[PDB]
Structure formats: C-alpha cells, structure tokens
Image (tube, rainbow, N blue to C red; front, side, top):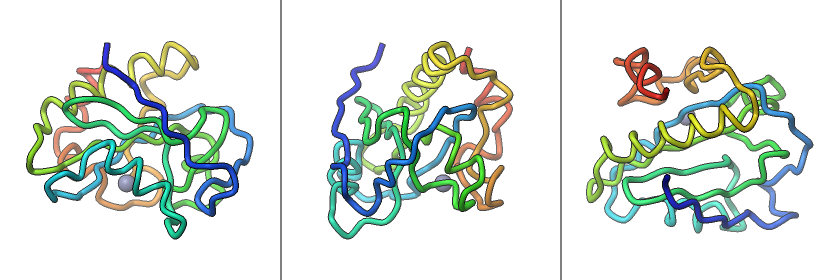
Length: 154
Ligand SMILES: [Zn+2]
C-alpha cells in the first residue's frame, strides 16, 4: 500500500475538460523528465499551472502517489484526440527524477495498477502503454521490457 495524495486540478482549468468517463483501459507513461525534484508532488503543482495543457490521473515516484483528476473524468495524455486513449482510460505517469529510484517508482506504479484493475474491473490486457494509442515512444524505459512490466503487476 502506497500513500495516495489527492490534488485535483481545479474545475475550470483548461487542462481539465470535465468530460464524463467510464475507464476501460489504463495507459502507462514515463515523464521523461530527469531533472532533480521532478517528482509526483512536482507534477501535481505543474498540472495546476493555469497555462498547462496536458493532464492525467496519477503520477508515481519512488516515495508516493498523486491524483490530479477524479476517475470519472478524462484527461489529455494519450495524444489520440477523442480516441479511447484520452476518452476511456486512466492515465498514469512514472517519474524519472535523477534524485529518485525508477525501480522503486515502478514497483509503486505496479501496485497502483493492480488496485485500479480490481476497482474498475479492467483486464490486464487493457493495461497498455501510451505507444498503443499515438505510436510515440512512451513509456521509454519500460517499452523494451514491457511484457515483463505487466507480468509484475499481479
Ligand atoms: Zn506518454
């Protein structure tokens, strides 16, 4: 059990569409941000920035987890417009801050996905990477061994 801090993007913000959502998929991402301090809390603040344009539900680092959006709304992260990526899936971001431990962040993320699958009846097969929707190289550090990553969710 990892601690999940809720810090919802305010209603009204540009990056919070508010469109109703019934998640059927779960999209895994990698911030691709190696800067020091670029953790979960950092992304929560970043997302509440009035000029931010993207948005997702969870951000994971080696220490804890932040929720930016309710699970009944969508976010912009799968880069596939109104496709199921953005409109029917829970977006999760795994931090890569050089001052943290990616392996530990991944273990925390695997726990979150497992719990998320049980609460919204989402099969392991519907746990896909960002690359599944837009074809972009994301999660970069996870793609190479993607099958092994899912095998560890349990
Ligand atoms: Zn991504």
